[PDB]
Image (tube, rainbow over all chains, first blue to last red; front, top):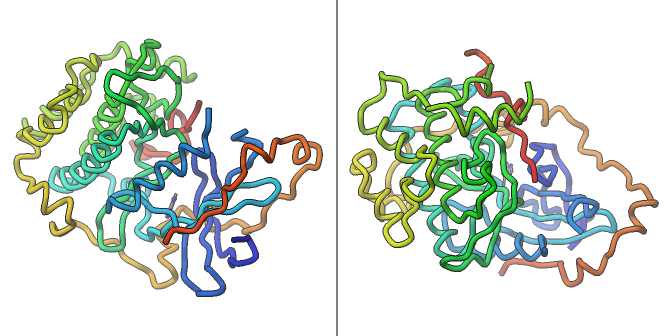
Length: 329
Length: 16
Ligand SMILES: Nc1ncnc2[nH]cnc12
C-alpha cells in the first residue's frame, strides 16, 4: 500500500529501530499501530527476519501480528495490530509494585510466547518492560522484533552482542556463543522488576554502561525477603548466571521445568494459552483511543515525518528491499 | 526509589 492510504494520528513510541505511530486506514477507518524504520538503519537480512517473525505472530495470541507492509524511498512501514492497553513500563510507573499473583499471570503469558518463538528457531533478544503490551482485556502481547534472531536449529548458537543492557544475559557479556537461554534470563530480570518494583541492579533506577555490565557479572542479586519462597526461588532459578543450569534452559525439558516450578504450579497452562484465564487487571480505556495509556513525551509530538536528505536517500541500495510490500489475508 | 523505572534512561536503551 502507501502512506497516503493512512491517516497519521499520533506518535505513541520510540522502538528499537522504529518510531511507532497510531494510524487509521482511511479506506476503512480501522485503527492500527505503525512501525516506521529508516532504511538508513537496515541496509545479514533484517527485513527477512522481521517478516519471518511476523509470520509466526499470526498464530499466537501473545504476539502482535502484521496487517501490512510498504515502503517510501527513505523508510520501511509495518502496519501492526493496535494494543491500546499500554506497556508494562507504563504499568509499573503507575502501579509501583505488582503482587505475586499479577506477576505470575504476566510471566506465564510471556513464557508461552517465548517458548512459541523458541520452538520455531527464534531468539527474541529484546525482552523488556517496554516491549510487553497490555490488551484492552488485560492479556499481554510481545511487540518489537527488531533484535530477533531466526533460523536457529538445535545446537545452533549465535554470538551477536545486542539487547538492552539492563536485561543482557551474563553469557553475552562474557562474549560466549548463546541460544534461547538469554530470553529466560531477561524474563528473570523482568519478573524481579514486577515483584520488587525496581531493577535487580541498583544503579539502574538511581556512570557508564560498562560498569552496569560489571555489576551484572559480579554482584550476587539480593531478593527482597518479603517475597514468598516460591517467588524468590523462581527468580534465583532464572537469574542463575550459568546458562547451563538456568531455569528453562535445558535443551529437552526447559519449558516443562518452568511449568513444573512451584511458582507456576498455580497455572493451568492450556486454559492460559487459550486466553480463558481472567486477567488480574483490566486496563482503563479512555475512549480517546486509550492514548492516556501512552507516555506523553510521545503523544505530545507532531506526527510529522522528518524530510529525507537526498545525499543519503540516493546512497542506499533499494535492491535489498525488493518485493517488500505485503498484506496479511 | 521514585525514579525506579525511567523510560529510555540509563541501561534501558536498546543497542547492537
Ligand atoms: N503494536 C503496538 N501497539 C501499541 N504500542 C506499541 N508500541 C510498540 N508497538 C506497539
